[PDB]
Image (cartoon, rainbow over all chains, first blue to last red; front, side, top):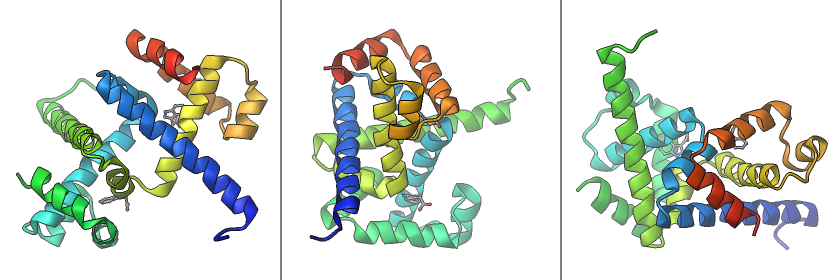
Amino acid sequence: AQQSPYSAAMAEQRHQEWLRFVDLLKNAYQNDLHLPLLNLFLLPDEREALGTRVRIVEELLRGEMSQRELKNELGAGIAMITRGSGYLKAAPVELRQWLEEVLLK
Amino acid sequence: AQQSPYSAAMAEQRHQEWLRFVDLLKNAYQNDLHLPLLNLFLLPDEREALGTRVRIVEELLRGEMSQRELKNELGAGIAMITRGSGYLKAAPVELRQWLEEVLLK
Ligand SMILES: O=C(O)Cc1c[nH]c2ccccc12
Ligand SMILES: O=C(O)Cc1c[nH]c2ccccc12
């Protein structure tokens, strides 16, 4: 319907594969195997990017850090700030409010 | 290139930033917010890569697919298979045993 069968079939396969990762990691957390699982599946630079993205989201929500501090401290230029801001705007409000509670105390 | 206090301090700061993401995601799984959280923090191509890496690891552990089949079906050339094989060999025994259990049924 929304996609032609070739595109739909590939998208469904990718969706199943993504959820398989999500469920594997879900159970790894319950078994205290999440740290080595994430070391296996994410490269060091990918893990660093995730740590830095959390700080970018935190500082965007907090509102105190300047654009130039975002670049110099977190490597986030104008375009990245605009993309990150867009992701926050697109997220469910419930997630955004939860992030505020957890990341901002 | 023996580590200096400067480099050690920055490495520990990056480590704490990574653990902060890990804990944030742990708590999102507990509140059923992991799916929107992962859409915020990972780009689509990064999510696809994680889904494909799970299949690569599964098929490496199962040992049935050939190198040509891994390339054709999963996009994993010989260099990536060598890296992935090395990550599995370096994983802690508890993780390798668990992955064999859950990925191979
Ligand atoms: O080595 C890479 O290019 C990325 C990567 C990270 N973890 C992996 C597990 C299996 C296959 C590839 C990867
Ligand atoms: O847009 C990017 O360059 C990657 C990215 C994904 N989620 C983010 C959240 C905050 C800042 C950057 C990103």
